[PDB]
Image (cartoon, rainbow, N blue to C red; front, side, top):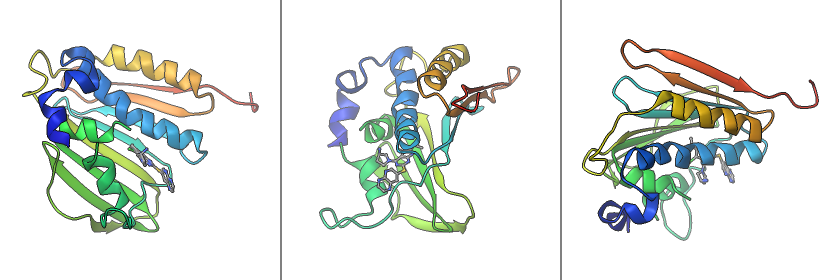
Length: 191
Ligand SMILES: CCc1[nH]c2nc(Sc3cnc4nccnc4c3)nc(N3CC[C@@H](N)C3)c2c1Cl
């Protein structure tokens, strides 16, 4: 399964250079965009964390957490563990954690180099809804660079806001000595 992704990442993300590093972000962001298209997500935050890890936060419905008859596993686990790019991001990260905010509960699971740490667990109560995915790209895969380009991300985030008119989407850099944030929103009929 995902071991094939770790051994031939070039076949899944096109490059293991800086281009592939940035592709990981879009693979997660695209899923949040799909949930905006479904009509439920209204805002997406992309964050470059101080350690060059990535957090993507949306306010959609939250990935389904119920057990599937075909797998006997929660749907959210399958999203990240079965090879449509979320599992690819998981495989090529040292760690990925998902929090699903749904029906008053926060459901949490984490993976390490693609492998499950523990069963999905309720860790908190919540009044919000959505999905938060955080990942640390694997330097064993991204041997050229693990350092993100804020302008590169910002440029595409702006493009995505335009193509998805009505969406709120932001990009934030939390790295030392260069903290920045840009927020984008193109108006619909209310304009
Ligand atoms: C933060 C990134 C994110 N946000 C996400 N938000 C949702 S919300 C959602 C999507 N589809 C549904 N279909 C049926 C019922 N509930 C749904 C909720 N789903 C997700 N899935 C599900 C399948 C795959 N596209 C990933 C994601 C993902 Cl990944």
